[PDB]
Image (cartoon, rainbow, N blue to C red; front, side, top):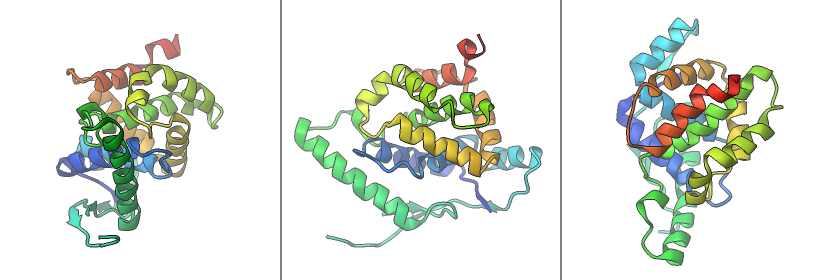
Length: 219
């Protein structure tokens, strides 16, 4: 049973990535999965199922819909995911709202590029996935330090924008997800090939394409 989000929930997943990125000392236990859910929503449900079936995996596709969940504590829009509980999703939102308020007080109005809903949030998470994927050939988690060294350089502007962009934690989460769910390696690679075809004004889409290509990695 694997969740296959369609284009309709891409904006939601993008915001979920952004919520983790704005969280001070964020718990990145689910970031690998969330990043992979974003990649799948970018491919769309049909192409995801096609990749999975063509790679030889048997897939029981779970539809992903947005539901309103009532849980009034000290007073939520969630996705129907077999892989991620309503509780986990709501706690990600709660913790980010706390980090948002700290940010709004400190500097007044939060600039677009420092928000949880910046269009490029999902791609910032996928940039770490691109680095881990490069090192995955090794067969172990040996390449994690090189992932941190490389991230700290290529994502310098993004780390400056997001307190929750913790390469060590995010890289560990992706290593975990690719080890635990190898079908995500196939999904990520097809996402990367499809993505690196697009050409736009987004700085992070450009950084991702360069990271995925890894022309300097082979050389």
